Image 1: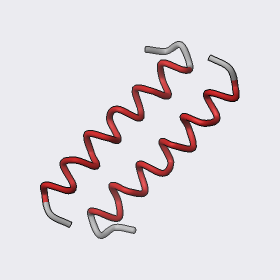
Image 2: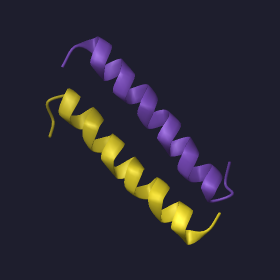
Image 3: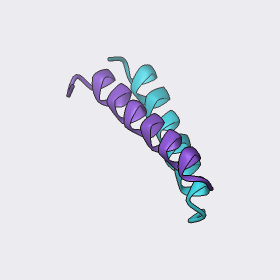
Length: 27
Length: 27
């Protein structure tokens, strides 16, 4: 539960949102 | 942009949200 880990998982979340939106032709 | 791909990226998004929330001690 470190900030190191939270920060990593948040950035990976941001990437994965983008990946979905690109697959949807929205980004 | 297939549904195959959207469905995959959506499920990966769901997993990654969960991963963040577990790192945050919220799940």
